[PDB]
Image (tube, rainbow, N blue to C red; front, side, top):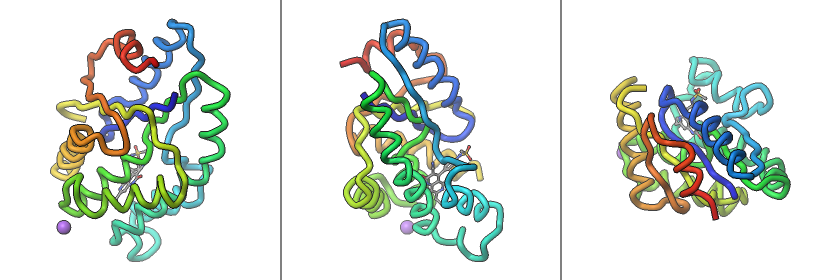
Length: 186
Ligand SMILES: CCc1cc2[nH]c(=O)c(C#N)c(-c3ccc(NS(C)(=O)=O)cc3)c2c(C)n1
Ligand code: NA
């Protein structure tokens, strides 16, 4: 089973990934995890992070440019992801493809039915062949540009409400991991 944990920065995603891992293992299930972006391993990731800090000219001015780099990062790990899905009962990703839909849409003042979010699907799932997650779990918290961060949180909620790329659950900071693991299990 492939699960992606999503949300804005400071939502506490990694804490949830770890809480979920423990719960799945307590339930008898093997777990492996990966985090995106793969800063330090992916040149595309690194150039993207670097662009957001003003390097690489006018690169960061293009939403689709940044989205492409982050996509290329994930596409590089496609064989790793498919390997974990064979080796383990549950693979949890700290960020996945929906990060690209939410952050790009938000920046472009588009909604989840908009062009960018659709493009992301065409590019990452169809073209680049990234597997669709069985579940995407949005961690939605009150407080993690802040208007952009809150707009991203909202668009996330909209991907969840529309079942973008598959089934979602939306959860809070205090969700019970044992109960969440039971809901996610096949
Ligand atoms: C310009 C539009 C745009 C598109 C994006 N697409 C992605 O796929 C993606 C991812 N993953 C991110 C991203 C990367 C790191 C983050 N947070 S972090 C690890 O704590 O630095 C938060 C978001 C992303 C961003 C920031 N912006
Ligand atoms: Na727009």
